[PDB]
Length: 310
Length: 39
Ligand SMILES: [Br-]
Ligand SMILES: [Br-]
Ligand SMILES: [Cl-]
Ligand code: NA
Image (cartoon, rainbow over all chains, first blue to last red; front, side, top):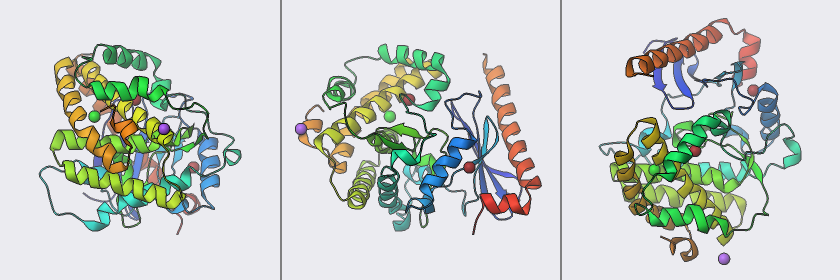
């Protein structure tokens, strides 16, 4: 627990993360297993920081420097806690209002991030798929194969949202800066919340950032059962995003959001089936996500046009 | 990779990241510290 020593380790399929206690606070580092151009280099991270710096998103953005092509080090934060510690908490503990308010602040932060003009971010790549899948095309194909082997009757509403439903939205809409990996494990909770990561950032659909954040609410509702708490967090996120932007999400935006969220759930369960040779456990996860998703999308404000697909 | 191999890889990758962050923290100068951690 001493200064200079690791207090948290978060391994993952695509990125390893460590929180080192230091004299001035808590220092997050991340490594990726391959040096790949899909991950933002030093110049792209600088360009993005420069674009964020004069905006109201600056306070939240904890953008790292690179030690090497595979290794990032973040500005110090004041706690080793992560929003995911609350979202996936089991058993329940007392609701901390300032932690819950992080969701409204994140929605506002994302609205501001998504308003940065593309001309200010010339170094950022168009994200046609997540950075981690572009860096590892063999993993992408394997996950896609495992996803194809999922029982199509396990989650028919999720399948509709990810497939036919997603395709109904127009393809022409403003692409924006996206964080690209906005899971609750990349957020330091409020007061004064901070957003970590950034090497997956680029230019893509802003709805994909909101979907990625909502996926943790669906997964935790399904796995731990605090459905009402997760629904309230979803509602707060939408409230903050719409208030900051000044306009409600359109039906098309909700269709795209639900498609990214449903696809993300399928990717998550397919990864469990393929990473851990567990087709039957992934099926159980998928059936629970099918039951948890409608309430979360409803709380987020999705219309019957979306929620009609189940 | 077997389970023993996967665990060996994960242990090595984690320790290497810890060592890199420790090295960077130890050696960063006040001017580099000023750019990454502003007040
Ligand atoms: Br930077
Ligand atoms: Br994915
Ligand atoms: Cl899930
Ligand atoms: Na419509």
